[PDB]
Amino acid sequence: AAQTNAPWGLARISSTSPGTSTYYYDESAGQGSCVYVIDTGIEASHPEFEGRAQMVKTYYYSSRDGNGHGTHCAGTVGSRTYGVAKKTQLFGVKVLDDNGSGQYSTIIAGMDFVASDKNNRNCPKGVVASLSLGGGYSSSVNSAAARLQSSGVMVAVAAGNNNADARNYSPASEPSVCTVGASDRYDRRSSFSNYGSVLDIFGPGTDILSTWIGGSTRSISGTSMATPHVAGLAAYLMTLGKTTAASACRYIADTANKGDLSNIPFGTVNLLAYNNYQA
Ligand SMILES: CN(C)c1ccc(C(N)c2ccc(N(C)C)cc2)cc1
Ligand SMILES: [Ca+2]
Ligand SMILES: [Ca+2]
């Protein structure tokens, strides 16, 4: 399959070179996989999700995404137009308030929730969790991410947006999950992207067009936008049977575009997520 005039990020993950505008992907499109987006919620009624999204848990008064961030991330995972895995199903877990903030205890609860909840869902091709959030180092936040990964879920987390070593941020600093840095359309490390030896992979993160609340769309930037590209790609690869939840981060790194990125500090991986699609 091919999507013409795709958002640049989608094109980039299906090309060995920057500058292309077509997203090439297998028609299976992540069907049979499930991705939990742990964030400010998801506007499930957005036409772009085609009824494939639903809220399963909130830690606040409502399950509504009153912010937009969660809906944007979910759109990059699995919306029709802006999504990597266009037939996956999406589950929203609202651990962040409508200001985009949340306490560590709530975030931890949301991760434990997913580890249990996945046992009540029909996801024959596997389960992914996308965490576009983070804060200062916390061993208990890292431990919750490690548990989620251990339980059989492919955990993708944002590196953070402080142009600093991700070792001082959580859950980015948890080695057992897949920590994702951001790149721009010219194959440079995004100016805000964290870096460091704990990074596993880079994905498109600068000027990412996706779904927004009120049935709208907008372009925003962050390692928050890179993470759902990798989460979507994981779901896509699991559906194809190329990898499992336990080994998906390693498979993505193994099959990545290598050495294409500029402005990568010594000690940080030069690896950009790539779907290896061959028609
Ligand atoms: C410091 N830390 C762990 C962290 C910081 C920022 C973010 C992030 N999602 C973010 C930060 C800034 C902005 N802007 C627009 C300033 C957007 C997203 C995530 C983690
Ligand atoms: Ca290349
Ligand atoms: Ca890792």
Image (tube, rainbow, N blue to C red):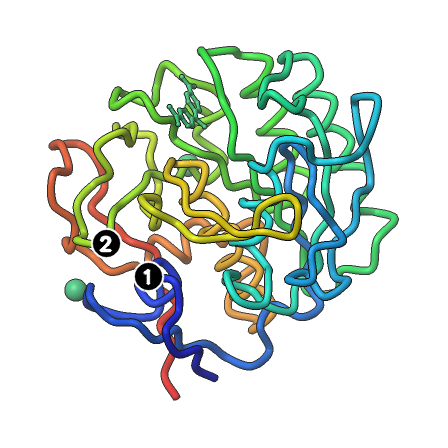
| Crowd rating for badge 1 (residues with CA inside 10 Å; few <14, some 14–19, many 20+) | many
**Residue 254: quadrant of the picture:** bottom left
Q: In percent of the image, x 29 and y 32: which residue is there?
A: 193
Q: Earlier in the sequence, mark 1 or mark 2?
A: 1
| Crowd rating for badge 2 (residues with CA inside 10 Å; few <14, some 14–19, many 20+) | some
Q: Which residue is mark 1?
A: 8
Image-based side of 193 in relation to 100, left or right:
left
Q: Which residue is mark 2?
A: 185
Q: Amino acid at mark 2?
A: Arg
Q: Amino acid at mark 1?
A: Trp
Which disc, if any, is residue 81? none
Where's the C terminus, which quadrant?
A: bottom left
Q: Is residue 254 above or below residue 41?
A: below
Image-based side of 252 in relation to 153, left or right:
left
Is the distance from the Cβ of mark 2 to the nearest ligand 2 atom less than 8 Å? no
Q: For numbered disc 1, what is the local secondary structure?
A: helix
Residue 214 or 251: which is nearer the viewer? 214
Residues tagged 1 and 2 counted as in contact (Cβ below 8 A)? yes
**Residue 110: quadrant of the picture:** top right
Q: Position of residue 206 (x, y in %)?
A: 31, 44
Q: Is residue 43 above or below residue 123?
A: above
Q: In percent of the image, x 34 and y 47: which residue is there?
A: 207
Determine the CA span between mark 1 and mark 2: 7 Å
Q: Position of residue 168 (x, y in %)?
A: 36, 14
Q: Position of residue 15 (x, y in %)?
A: 28, 70
Q: For numbered disc 2, what is the local secondary structure?
A: loop
**Residue 45: quadrant of the picture:** bottom right
Q: In percent of the image, x 65 and y 34: which residue is there?
A: 148
